[PDB]
């Protein structure tokens, strides 16, 4: 086991052996941005791709080409921590190599001049932190992945609402990544219409006309021919028997001398077999049959030249006679089977008004730009650039792969531009499905829904910047002269960097980190949003989209989603899932070799999963990968059933892979209704870090993975031994094995103490380890917020009893004992930030001095001479945080603009920061802050130098001992007196000058490094135009739990703390221990969350064991007893994958482990492979507790016994962020709004309640006329009315003076101001 | 532009503003409160009533000027709290909860100063507010002028609004903890401590129970004096020995004078308590009902706490015969599937068979579990043994009506039935496991889908409701009761709607509180039962059930003659109060709210079979008896009603043209006897006379196609 694991082992239930370990949970973000930067030769995904896409930039036929070589990411100027402190964006400079080449002009082009630009600076790109986030202005932002429809072609149905007469009208949509959209739809009359991206629907054939296809060519390509030969007389037809499928006979079908099908009887299978075996090709047919068909080609009279029938014209006897007399032996008619093969392109051609290519292009042009006369070449160029221009129309590699796969073409790699064969095949498939030989696609299939992560969106935005700047360079290179200018006045970085920072900063998917819980961080980073750019808007989207598709299995969490209005549009990603090479979603599966379940894992996407039969994870395997049952339970096409042993292709990796991290943290998920599990997870992500987090008594084992993988813990990078421990830094001496040979030194981890998180919570790290303990690579040195010894401890575990106690827990409300507040276990620290900004006005700059007009010295007492509060001073609402004066001109004094503490907030000033970009004057506080940072830098550098210096001196002593041993005199004189000493002239003297010069070089490197650090510290941190300086002040406030606050469990049970009872009143067991929480039973039966009951039982068992060992340990019997007891406990049955034992060191580690477990041994029930009841019963028995898990309790107030014993035990509860002191609010009178004199809205400013129209109706239902009267005039809007009412109340009388509202009188004057006579009548 | 448009004026100006002297905070239980009061935090009360405080402080002379009043309030000295206490005595405040669906969403209470930052809300009214203690917050307004105060105390106070304006029933009925406690209190046990001793009254019953010399429920003979106001408002004591439990006597202590003892003698569940309150209100009046409800709450809470009811893992008993049922149903599904693979049954037929057999197995297991759990306490008396309604805590929570229904009990201990896939089709294999046991990935996943769909439905339903109710309240706002009586004779003849099998809804409730259009006569003329228009209160309604009035013409609002409004008489009485409507109340808005707010939880026939023994009567028919001896139905609008022994129409059916009949008129039909017959998917055309069929305008070929079979007389002549 690891060292932190050996510290406190967690008793793990769970039967199936974990084959795959949980991957790095933040893989998505880091891997995507790595792919984004990813210096690579062959243009694959990556910035490189964008450059090669946009370059080469050739002049407007000016023969001055621009070429791209390569780019380089500059080293960031600001590290992460200092960047947060100083309020700048953490970024790297981007530099690109270009060449300008000028060839022969008015001559065959030949390279005349080539100039190389000196590594042009092309702007700043923000870098991503180690944890996978972005610091954009000293605020931690996250870029959520976006789920959206993949490029390609989709055949939709859109039925039901089509004219309410059935008539299912199909449609094919071609969507590219970049370029216009193509749409083919039908009409009630089965005519197939095309609609350019989002316009009206035109007949499709016009586009076919634009592609240069003649009507006969089209009818050739689409319709099945029917041949009519005339041999010596009367119209004999060449017939393929198999064409007759499903056709009532219209004529008498005689053949070879024998009538086969009588005229009128539909051809039966008997006749079909007869005719087939007879081998009948041609049959003479009556002229009435042909008197109805349609002609395919445009048969002209070859002899004379006169046209007779046109392409797709109905046949009449006269036309048949003309054709027969003209001498046409071979006739090609159309096959119109009114059942299967319809005349769709024919009828579209009939409705199609355009005839020539030119008329089609004219109509097209008149569609895009209606009203301006279309010129031929304009239409030609438009159509060319529409779908076949490499630059404007590009689908993708992914778009093209999906496109070819949808139409069943073997070739995966295509051209970006839309080729003609693509469109023709698409139309063929559309008409095919229209006949019914095909299925429509379902949008909700994850095989049709692709995930765009950060790097892809950043790449797109950067490309946009590039296309802009390319146009710019193009024009400047065209107009301006060619050879005078060098390639840096010409290219401007400002708009590109502007676009990148707008995207990263001001975007829908780029949002503030939800930073109060480690779980909150980890779940926020692994999120998939369907909104944003190219994302569905919430209101129009249908219920069908927000349902859970069977494809989501093992890819997205079914249970974790906000329960607000956008439920189902968020869908947090599952544990084990990954992104494909093309941005699809894949999940791991174990291969199945016919009998044995092997150990190699393959990642499968949605489509591949669809085909196979996948076995469940909870299937019993004995020692060689064979299923115990003959018929096992699997799923094949999204539906589960029984399959045979020797049919399963794959098997689920583990039971946990269905659910997200949040859901995986809930114990006994298998016993909770899905609704309450959903709400439980959603709430559990809101828990606030307490003062000392401890641990869950009932966990799932995932706590350490979450804590480590989040960046809140401090984790060792190179293993070694802890040299120095302080409550600010941990300094570790590396082990010699891993110790780098040249210029290694030791490792130092600086910790972070109370700082403000996004949610105003405290972020503090505590050291775990002590002096002299050995640490290995990857152990947890320091605990972050709300984590203990590596484990996630969101809340705390307390002793609950399920009973109604005089209706104080009537509804879901909760009763709590005074011991919890006395022992201070639910008290949190919060942290507000306040900012005072001194800008430069045109009347004169404001000042920060402490000299503030007409303020009493009481207010100054807590201010220093510079005008900033002392660190540690206690302030209250309304106190002056800092002193500022606004200058007055045309005097500067007599008025104060000093910032004050907001009303009703009181805490201690823990920190102050000052930012003066100008650097004018500087200030006292800047000097103190600079010295605090500087002294630290000095200490660290001094420590490193002294270690390296001690080493150099040891080597100097080892050389000095050679060549004449001198050990008496040397060791007692100071060490600095060893360089001035001498030795016999030899190579040894050469070594002494060498070592002296290396000592000097270490000094000089030290001095320059120090100078550099001091230059970085001193420089002004670039502020916005007009602001001289800014001072930020952090207040910290300790909030204790009180009645009205909200508390919850992990299973969805909620409540408001209703009353704090004295300890004596609370129920107590015979032993005298009072319970902590009194929980309502009536929440169980209707809210079928049974997981809390099992959790309570198992928690009592675990705390019982912990109590027994604490009791046995306080008496300190002997090591032997402890080892025996702990072993018997840890074994507890069989089938467990634990395997612990006493192999660990014999005395120290056991004593430490007992000390840590004495507070209760932590259990680990996995989600679905959990602890069954019998095991809980056994564990309760081992502790000497009632097996039924309920005990008899005596009422602490009255003393009589309760009938029917009650369930008690320990449950892990959380205090949610809904804290009563923020919610409570009241106003009598206060500030009103400027334009409409209504009271301000909000809590910061006093603010009134919104008396809506529904409340008006409620009051109107009663006869409450006077209440409404005051509500409309006296309470809000009437100025004179409100002051008169105030004065009347002050006078001690409670009346009012009625009349017409003045606003109404204003109305009279405004309406009267028109030519309208409106009079106030009287009687 | 200033006048027209939203932003300009009217549409925004006088539509939805923020008011003063208002606050908002979280609500909390506070059981010790009286029904007409509410717990209010000190600090909020001070902030709200600030100007009152200043006025009273200046009146008492404690402060020379107003600024001194502010300084003394910001120090918060004892005098300030004394003045605040003095001003608060009778001043009422308005409580509102964000979605004010109906007029009971705003009510006035008297505040009691308490510590803390949470508002304390009386439990009984939560049902009216639809309030839940899971972080719901509430708003609190202060009426300023004197008329507003008077209006709040008279019209809007909680105790004045006990009946819902929608229907007449009480709103403040005990909800969950109270009913559980009372249920525990009244149930009896075969054998306990203090079996069969005779007590002189309830007071020594309490002596016995509280001293632990007798169990709270144990059968006993007690002497009790009930009072009855049988005379013209005088109470007569009747005193006798009844056989009851100690608990029922203890409960009897509270019960006001007028009520018969019988009321408490039963198991006393939710319904029983509700009807108890109903009778108490109808007989005694408002104030006794209020005090009785408060007493019920206190005793229920107390004895529920003394009961100590909890929920352990062993409390939900898995039925012993579940596994057999599951194995049998699996074997049956396997046999039907194999017999499908051979191809004697379509896929749809197999689907239907599997779904039906699984449903049957589910019902079997549910009934077996309910039998096992319900009456399993086989506890022993002195000698032989006996069995009784069990004391299983979960069973008491189910049966009392406090929480949960049979369905959830099933969902805990049985198989959780069949599920529906997205499109509504039902999965072939059900979820055999239950929450006491553990589900597996597939079954969980399925239930997740279910819950997601359910919640989304509820969301959209709420949006649609809001929209509908807004239109309703908008359209009907102006209607007001302006006149006392228009004096019309018109009215609607109201009958009890007897849809098919029986009387879904009786007359008495349908007519209660409506004035009659004209006097109705007994089944014998000149026997006037009700004078010209009288308000039909409970006594008249009871009078109508002993007699057999079937249909009553009552004045309706639609036929009212009054111009520009309605008259009191045409409307009737029904209100939160009991009496005839008062001139001036805006009934349009109350009606619109009452119809809108509840709208948020809304998502073969071959032979007739008489259910109860009665005479058959045919209405609106003209039959012609044929040779077979059948009463041939020749009318499409024929009805067959059922007169009972005492002249009342129990069952009513509609008999179509061409249905074979058996019994005519007068015949008494035995229970469940087939009186009629006809082809379900076939309406035959019946000839009245005999002879040869003659074809007229029946030409062959033009409009009909002769497709005729051989001698046996089959044909396909089709008159299209
Ligand atoms: Mg709530
Ligand atoms: Zn009327």
Image: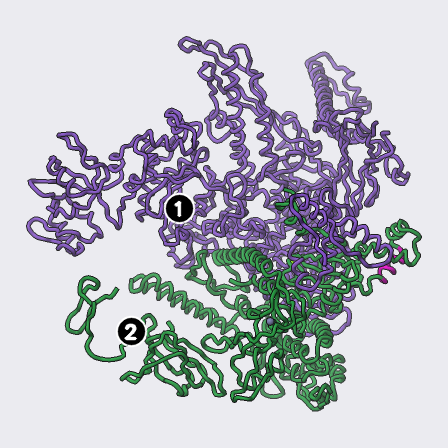
Q: Over which residues does the magenta segment extend?
A: B77-86
Q: Which mark is residue B685?
A: 2
Q: Nearer the viewer, mark 1 or mark 2?
A: 2
Quadrant location of the C terminus of chain B?
bottom left
Q: Quadrant of residue B52?
A: bottom right
Residue B511 among those drawn in magenta:
no
What subunit carries mark 2? B
Q: Which mark is residue A156?
A: 1
Nearer to me, A97 or A941 = A97
Specify the chain shown as green.
B
SS assignment at label 1 = strand
- Taking the image as four quarters, which one is ligand 1 found in? bottom right
Q: CA distance from mark 1 to mark 2?
A: 48 Å
Kindly identify the residue that appears in the image at 33 percent across and 47 percent down.
A189
Nearer to me, B321 or A740 = B321
Q: Pointer 2: residues within 10 angstroms few (<14), some, or many (20+)?
A: few
Q: Quadrant of residue B508?
A: bottom right
Does A797 appear above or below B269? above
Residue B82 among those drawn in magenta:
yes
Does A439 appear above or below A501? below
> Is residue A72 shown left or right of residue B62?
left
Q: Quadrant of residue B1?
A: top right
Q: Pointer 1: residues within 10 angstroms few (<14), some, or many (20+)?
A: some
Magenta stretch, main secondary structure class? helix
Q: What colour scheme was applied to this rendering of the protein?
A: by chain
Give the color of chain A as drawn.
purple
Residue A797 spot, x, y in % from top left = 68, 56
């Amino acid at each position: 086991y690891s060292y932190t694991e050996k510290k406190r082992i967690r008793k793990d239930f769970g039967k199936r052996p974990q084959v795959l370990d949980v991957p790095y949970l933040l893989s998505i973000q880091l891997d995507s941005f790595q792919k984004f930067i990813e210096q690579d030769p062959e243009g694959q995904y990556g910035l490189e791709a964008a450059f090669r896409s946009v370059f080469p930039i050739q002049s407007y036929s000016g023969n001055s080409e621009l070429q791209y070589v390569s780019y380089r990411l500059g080293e960031p100027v600001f590290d992460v921590q200092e960047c947060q402190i100083r309020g700048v964006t953490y970024s790297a400079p981007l530099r690109v190599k270009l060449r300008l080449v000028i060839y022969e002009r008015e001559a065959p082009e030949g390279t005349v001049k080539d100039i190389k630009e000196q590594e042009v600076y092309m702007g700043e790109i923000p870098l991503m932190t180690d944890n996978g986030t972005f610091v954009i202005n000293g605020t931690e932002r996250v870029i959520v992945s976006q789920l959206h429809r993949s490029p390609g072609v989709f055949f939709d149905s859109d039925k039901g609402k089509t004219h309410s007469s059935g008539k299912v009208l199909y449609n094919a949509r071609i969507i590219p990544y970049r370029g216009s959209w193509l749409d083919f739809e039908f009409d009630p009359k089965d005519n197939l219409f095309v609609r350019i991206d989002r316009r009206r629907k035109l007949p499709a054939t016009i586009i076919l006309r634009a592609l240069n296809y003649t009507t006969e060519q089209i009818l050739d390509l689409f319709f099945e021919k029917v041949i009519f030969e005339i041999r010596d007389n009367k119209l004999q037809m060449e017939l393929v028997p198999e064409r007759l499928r499903g056709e009532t006979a219209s004529f008498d079908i005689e053949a070879n001398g024998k009538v086969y099908v009588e005229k009128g009887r539909r051809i039966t299978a008997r006749h079909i077999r007869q005719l087939e075996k007879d081998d009948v090709k041609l049959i003479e047919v009556p002229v009435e049959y042909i008197a109805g068909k349609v002609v395919a080609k445009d048969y002209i009279d070859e002899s004379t030249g006169e046209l007779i029938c046109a392409a797709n014209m109905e046949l009449s006897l006269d036309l048949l006679a003309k054709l027969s007399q003209s001498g046409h032996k071979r006739i090609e008619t159309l096959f119109t089977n009114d059942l299967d093969h319809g005349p769709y392109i024919s009828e579209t051609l009939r409705v199609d008004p355009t005839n020539d290519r030119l008329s089609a292009l004219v109509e097209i042009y008149r569609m895009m730009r209606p009203g301006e006369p279309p010129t031929r070449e304009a239409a030609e160029s438009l159509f060319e650039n529409l779908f076949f221009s490499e630059d404007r129309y590009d689908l993708s590699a992914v778009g093209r792969m999906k496109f070819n796969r949808s139409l069943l073409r073997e070739e995966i790699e295509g051209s970006g531009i839309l080729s003609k064969d693509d469109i023709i095949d698409v139309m063929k498939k559309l008409i095919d499905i229209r006949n019914g030989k095909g299925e429509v696609d379902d949008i909700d299939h994850l095989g049709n829904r692709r995930i765009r992560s950060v790097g892809e969106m950043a790449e797109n935005q950067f490309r946009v910047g590039l296309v802009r700047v390319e146009r710019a360079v193009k024009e400047r290179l065209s107009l301006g002269d060619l050879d005078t200018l060098m390639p840096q006045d010409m290219i401007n970085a400002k708009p590109i960097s502007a676009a990148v920072k707008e995207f990263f900063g001001s975007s829908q998917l780029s949002q503030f980190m939800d930073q109060n819980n480690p779980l909150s961080e980890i779940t926020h980073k692994r999120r998939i949003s369907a909104l944003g750019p190219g994302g569905l808007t919430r209101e129009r989207a249908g219920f069908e989209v927000r349902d859970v598709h069977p494809t989501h299995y093992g890819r997205v969490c079914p249970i974790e989603t906000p329960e607000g209005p956008n439920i189902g549009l968020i869908n947090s990603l599952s544990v084990y899932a990954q992104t494909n090479e093309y941005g699809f979603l894949e999940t791991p599966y174990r291969k199945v070799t016919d009998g044995v379940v092997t150990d190699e894992i393959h990642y499968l996407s949605a489509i591949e999963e669809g085909n196979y039969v996948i076995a469940q994870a909870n299937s019993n395997l004995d020692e060689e990968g064979h299923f115990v049952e003959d018929l096992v339970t699997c799923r094949s096409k999204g539906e589960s059933s029984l399959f045979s042993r020797d049919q399963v292709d794959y098997m689920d990796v583990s039971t946990q892979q269905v659910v997200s991290v949040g859901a995986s943290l809930i114990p006994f998920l298998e016993h909770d209704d899905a609704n309450r599990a959903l709400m439980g997870a959603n709430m559990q992500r809101q828990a606030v870090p307490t003062l000392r987090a401890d641990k869950p008594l009932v966990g799932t084992g995932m706590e350490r993975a979450v804590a480590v993988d989040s960046g809140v813990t401090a984790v060792a990078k190179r293993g070694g031994v802890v040299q120095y421990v302080d409550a600010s830094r941990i300094v570790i001496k590396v082990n010699e094995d891993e110790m780098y040979p040249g210029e290694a030194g030791i490792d130092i981890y600086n910790l972070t103490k109370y700082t403000r998180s996004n949610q105003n919570t405290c972020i503090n790290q505590m050291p775990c380890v002590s002096l002299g303990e050995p640490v290995e690579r990857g152990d947890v040195l320091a605990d972050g917020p709300s984590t203990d010894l590596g484990e996630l401890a969101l809340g705390q575990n307390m002793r609950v009893a399920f009973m109604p106690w005089n209706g104080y827990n009537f509804e879901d409300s909760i009763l709590v004992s005074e011991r919890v507040v006395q022992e201070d276990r639910f008290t949190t620290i919060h942290i507000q930030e306040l900012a005072c900004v001194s800008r430069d006005t045109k009347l004169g700059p404001e000042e920060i001095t402490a000299d503030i007009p007409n303020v009493g010295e009481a207010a100054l007492s807590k201010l220093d001479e510079s005008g900033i509060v002392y660190i540690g001073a206690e302030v209250t609402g309304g106190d002056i945080l800092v002193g500022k004066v606004t200058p007055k001109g045309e005097a500067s004094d007599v008025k104060d603009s000093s910032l004050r503490v907001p009303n009703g907030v009181s805490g201690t000033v823990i920190d102050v920061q000052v930012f003066t970009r100008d650097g004018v004057e500087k200030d006292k506080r800047a000097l103190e802050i600079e010295e605090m940072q500087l002294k630290q830098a000095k200490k660290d550098l001094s420590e490193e130098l002294q270690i390296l210096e001690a080493g150099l001196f040891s080597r100097i002593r080892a050389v000095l001992v050679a060549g004449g041993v001198e050990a008496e005199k040397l060791d007692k004189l100071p060490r600095d007196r060893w360089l001035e000493l001498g030795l016999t002239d030899e190579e040894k003297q050469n070594q002494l000058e060498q070592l002296a010069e290396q000592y000097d070089e270490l000094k000089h490197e030290f001095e320059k490094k120090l100078e550099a650090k001091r230059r970085k510290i001193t420089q002004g941190d670039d502020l916005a135009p007009g602001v001289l300086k800014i001072v930020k002040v952090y207040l910290a406030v300790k909030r204790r739990i009180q009645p009205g606050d909200k508390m919850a469990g992990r299973h969805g049970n909620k409540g408001v703390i209703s009353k704090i009872n004295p300890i004596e009143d609370m129920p107590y067991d015979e032993n005298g221990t009072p319970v902590d929480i009194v929980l309502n039973p009536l929440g169980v039966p209707s809210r079928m969350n049974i997981g809390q009951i099992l959790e309570t039982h198992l928690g009592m068992a675990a705390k019982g064991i912990g109590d027994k060992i604490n009791a046995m340990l306080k008496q300190q019997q002997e090591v032997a007893k402890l080892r025996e007891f702990i072993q018997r406990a840890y074994d507890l049955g069989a089938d467990v994958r634990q395997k612990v034992d006493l192999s660990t060191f014999s005395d120290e580690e056991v004593m430490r482990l007992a000390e840590n477990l004495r507070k209760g041994m932590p259990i680990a029930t996995p989600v679905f492979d959990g602890a069954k009841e019998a095991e809980i019963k056994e564990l309760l028995k081992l502790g000497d507790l009632p097996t039924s898990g309920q005990i008899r309790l005596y009422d602490g107030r009255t003393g009589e016994q309760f009938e029917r014993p009650v369930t008690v035990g320990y449950m892990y509860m959380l205090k949610l962020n809904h804290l009563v002191d923020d919610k409570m609010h009241a106003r009598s009178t206060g500030s009103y709004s400027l334009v409409t004199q209504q009271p301000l809205g909000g809590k910061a400013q006093f603010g009134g309640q919104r008396f809506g129209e529904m409340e008006v109706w409620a009051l109107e239902a009663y006869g409450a006329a006077y209440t409404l009267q005051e509500m409309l005039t006296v309470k809000s809007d009437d100025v004179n009315g409100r002051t008169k009412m105030y004065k009347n109340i002050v006078d001690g009388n409670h009346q009012m003076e009625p009349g017409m509202p003045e606003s109404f009188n204003v109305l009279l004057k405004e309406i009267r101001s028109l030519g309208i006579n409106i009079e106030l009548e009287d009687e | 532009d200033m006048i027209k448009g939203k932003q300009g004026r009217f549409r925004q100006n006088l539509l939805g503003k923020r008011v003063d002297y208002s606050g908002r905070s979280v609500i909390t239980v506070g059981p010790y409160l009286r029904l007409h009061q509410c717990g209010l935090p000190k600090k909020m009360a001070l902030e709200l009533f600030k100007p009152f405080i200043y006025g009273k402080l200046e009146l008492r002379g404690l402060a020379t000027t107003i600024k001194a009043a502010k300084k003394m309030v910001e120090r918060e000295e004892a005098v300030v709290w004394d003045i605040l206490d003095e001003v608060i005595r009778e001043h009422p405040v308005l409580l509102n909860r964000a979605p004010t669906l109906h007029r009971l969403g705003i009510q006035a209470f008297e505040p009691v100063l308490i510590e803390g930052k949470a508002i304390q809300l009386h439990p009984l009214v939560c049902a009216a507010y639809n309030a839940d203690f899971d972080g719901d917050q509430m708003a609190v307004h202060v009426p300023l002028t004197l008329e507003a105060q008077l209006e709040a105390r008279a019209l809007m106070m909680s105790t004045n609004n006990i009946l819902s304006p929608a229907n007449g029933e009480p709103i403040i009925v005990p909800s969950q903890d109270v009913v559980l406690g009372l249920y525990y209190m009244t149930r009896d046990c075969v054998n306990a401590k203090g079996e069969g001793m005779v007590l002189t009254g309830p007071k020594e019953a309490e002596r016995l129970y509280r001293s632990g010399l007798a169990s709270l429920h144990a059968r006993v003979k007690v002497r009790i004096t009930e009072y009855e106001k049988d005379a013209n408002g005088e109470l007569v004591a009747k005193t006798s020995l009844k056989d009851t439990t100690v608990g029922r006597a203890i409960l009897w202590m509270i019960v006001p004078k007028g009520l018969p003892y019988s009321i408490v003698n039963q198991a006393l569940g939710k319904k029983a308590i509700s009807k108890m309150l109903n009778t108490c209100y109808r007989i005694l009046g408002l104030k006794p009902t209020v005090i009785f409800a408060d007493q019920i709450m206190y005793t229920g809470f107390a004895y529920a706490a003394r009961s100590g009811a909890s929920v352990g893992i062993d409390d939900m008993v898995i039925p012993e015969k579940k596994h057999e049922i599951i194995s049998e149903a699996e074997a049956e599904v396997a046999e039907i599937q194999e017999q499908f693979q051979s191809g004697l049954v379509t896929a749809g037929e197999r689907y239907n068979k599997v779904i039906d057999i699984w449903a049957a197995a589910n019902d079997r297991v549910s009934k077996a579990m309910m039998d096992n759990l319900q009456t399993e306490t086989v506890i022993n008396r002195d000698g032989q043994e006996e069995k009784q309604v069990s004391f299983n805590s979960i069973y008491m929570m189910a049966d009392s009506g406090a929480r949960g229904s049979a369905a959830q009990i099933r969902q805990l201990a049985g198989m959780r039935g069949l599920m529906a896939k997205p499109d509504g089709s039902i999965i072939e294999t059900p979820i055999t496991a239950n929450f006491r046991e553990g589900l597996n990935v597939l079954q969980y996943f399925i239930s997740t889908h279910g819950a997601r769909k359910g919640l989304a439905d509820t969301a959209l339903k709420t949006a649609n409701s809001g929209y509908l109710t807004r239109r309703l309240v908008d359209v009907a706002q102006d209607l007001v009761v302006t006149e006392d009586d228009c004096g019309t004779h018109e009215g609607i003849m109201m009958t009890p709607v007897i849809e098919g099998g029986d009387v879904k809804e009786p007359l008495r409730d349908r007519v209660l509180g409506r004035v009659t259009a004209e006097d109705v006569l007994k089944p014998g003329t000149a026997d006037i039962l009700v004078p010209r228009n009288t308000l039909l209160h409970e006594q008249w309604c009871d009078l109508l059930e002993e007699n057999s009035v079937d249909a009553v013409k009552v004045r309706s609002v639609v036929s009212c003659d009054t111009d520009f409004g309605v008259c009191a008489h045409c409307y009737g009485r029904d209100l939160a109060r009991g009496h005839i409507i008062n001139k001036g109340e805006a009934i349009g808005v109350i009606a619109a709210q009452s119809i809108g707010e509840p709208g948020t939880q809304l998502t073969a026939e071959s032979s007739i079979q008489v259910k109860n023994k009665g005479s058959i009567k045919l209405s609106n028919v003209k039959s012609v008896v044929n040779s077979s001896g059948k009463l041939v139905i020749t009318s499409r609008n024929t009805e067959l009603k059922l007169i009972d022994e005492f002249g009342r129409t129990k069952e009513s059916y509609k008999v179509p043209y061409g249905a074979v009949l058996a019994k005519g008129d007068g015949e008494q039909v035995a229970g469940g006897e087939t009186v009629a017959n006809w082809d379900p998917h076939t309406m035959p055309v019946i000839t009245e006379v005999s002879g040869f069929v003659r074809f007229t305008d029946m030409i062959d070929g033009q409009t009909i196609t002769r497709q005729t079979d051989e001698l046996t007389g089959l044909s396909s002549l089709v008159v299209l």
